[PDB]
Image: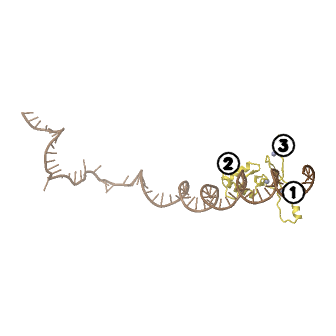
Chain colours: A yellow, B brown
Amino acid sequence: PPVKGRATRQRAAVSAALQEVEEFRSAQELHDMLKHKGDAVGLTTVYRTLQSLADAGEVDVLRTAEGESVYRRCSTGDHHHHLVCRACGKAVEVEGPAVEKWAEAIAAEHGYVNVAHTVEIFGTCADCAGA
DNA sequence: CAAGGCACATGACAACGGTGTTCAGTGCCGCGTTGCCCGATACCCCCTACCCGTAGTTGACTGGCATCCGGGCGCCGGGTCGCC
Ligand SMILES: [Zn+2]
Ligand SMILES: [Zn+2]
Ligand SMILES: [Zn+2]
């Protein structure tokens, strides 16, 4: 996980933590689990590295209803949409050219120069209903 | 003269006003700590220059050295050969 800044142990540690975690997480709870591992990193520094990862683009970023920004990394480079369960957090990556063509067609119809789509589908889990 | 009819105001009724606080999220500036990058420095190599130890050099050449006295002074102590 290369970063724009000079490599060191702490960015490697947070990158490895993101690698192990395959769920949507917030910065504060990410720091909580990171401290639980025992690295004892700083809050604001963790912010810098996660922000850098979001800027780099190798980690997707989502915004919750509460307004918190949450992050998680994706195995595949190409763009995709993550279906996520609020209770579980199971993020599954899917993509469809139909929505892309729809966006381009709308942009052309309205004479828009450039666009950027943000589509996230929320829903109820299959196993959450079961008990 | 008493009972029945209409005005204004009234006991509550929430919801705005405006402003103060709550978790929480994320930075914004202050203090301190970190990967680089090089640059010099200790430490292997090769070469030869020079110090230092060993071994020969065949006419003949076969025993030295200069001592030492003007203490001075007395005693100890032992050796040392005569003595009868
Ligand atoms: Zn993604
Ligand atoms: Zn998309
Ligand atoms: Zn679920």
Q: Residue at x 74, y 51 (%)?
A: A26
Question: In the rendered view, would you say B1 is above or below A112?
Answer: above
Q: Which mark is residue A35?
A: 2
Q: Secondary structure at mark 3?
A: helix
Q: Examine the image and state in which quarter residue A56 appears.
A: bottom right
Whether pointer 3 and pointer 1 mark residues with C-beta atoms closer than 8 Å, the reply is: no
Q: Nearer the viewer, residue A120 or B82?
A: A120
Look at label 3 and name its amino acid.
Ala
**For mark 3, what is the residue?**
A129
Relative to A68, B4 lies left or right: right
Tag 2: Cα neighbours inside 10 Å, few (<14), some, or many (≥20)? few
Q: Is residue A41 left or right of residue B70?
A: right
- Under circle 1, the secondary element is helix
Q: Nearer the viewer, residue B62 or B84?
A: B84
Residue A12 in picture, x, y percent from top left: 69, 52
The quarter of the image that holds ligand 1 is bottom right
Q: Amino acid at mark 1?
A: Val
Residue lying at 84% horizontally and 43% vertically, measured from the top left: A129
Chain designation of label 2: A
- For the point 88% across and 64% down, the residue is A108
**Is disc 3 surrounded by few (<14), some (14 to 19) or many (20+) residues within 10 Å?**
few
Decide if ligand 2 comes within 8 Å of the CB at mark 1: yes
Q: Position of residue A107 (x, y in %)?
A: 87, 63
Task: Kindly identify which residue carries mark 1.
Answer: A99
Q: CA distance from mark 3 to mark 1?
A: 30 Å
Amino acid marked by disc 2: Lys
Compared across the picture, whether B76 is left or right of A26 comes to left
- Distance from label 2 to label 1 (Cα)? 41 Å
